Image (cartoon, rainbow, N blue to C red):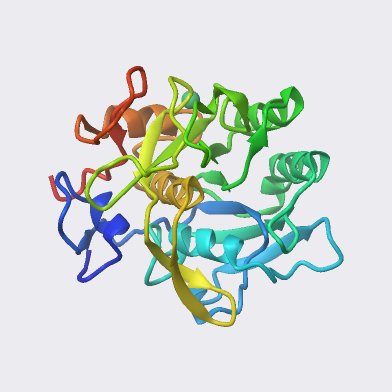
Length: 279
Ligand SMILES: [Ca+2]
């Protein structure tokens, strides 16, 4: 399949070189997988999701995304137009309020909640959890992500937006999950993106067009926007039979575009998520 004039990041994770705008992909498009977006929620009514999104939990007085963040990240995962894996099932878990603030212990709860709930869902092709959130370092927050991964969910986490070494941030530093740094449309590391030997992979993070609440779209930036590109890619790869939830971070690294980003500090992998479809 081909989707012309695509947001740059979808074209980028289907290309070897920057500077084009078509997204080349296999039409199975994540059918039969599932992705949990752990965030401010998902406006499931947004037609872009076409009936393929459900809130299934909240830790606040409402399950709605009243912030837009969770809706945008979810759109990059799996909206019809702006998503990677256009036919995956989406599940929302609202751990962030509407200003986009969550206490750790609520983030921990929602993470254990996925390890359990996946068992209430039909996801024959694999299950993925996309966490576009983080803060300082916590053994506990890290341990919750390592349980979610261990429970057979591919866990994708934002490396963080301070321009540092992500080894001081959580859940990013947790070593056993897949920590996602950011790039721009000219293959630069985004000027914020965190870096450090705990990163596994980069995906598109700077000027990412996706869904926003009210039915609407906006183009925002962050490792938060890079993270659901690599979650959706993993759903896409499960579904194709290439990899598995345990194995997907390694498979994505093995098949990445290798050398191609500017400003990988020393010591940070220079790897750019790639679907290997067109070549
Ligand atoms: Ca890893």
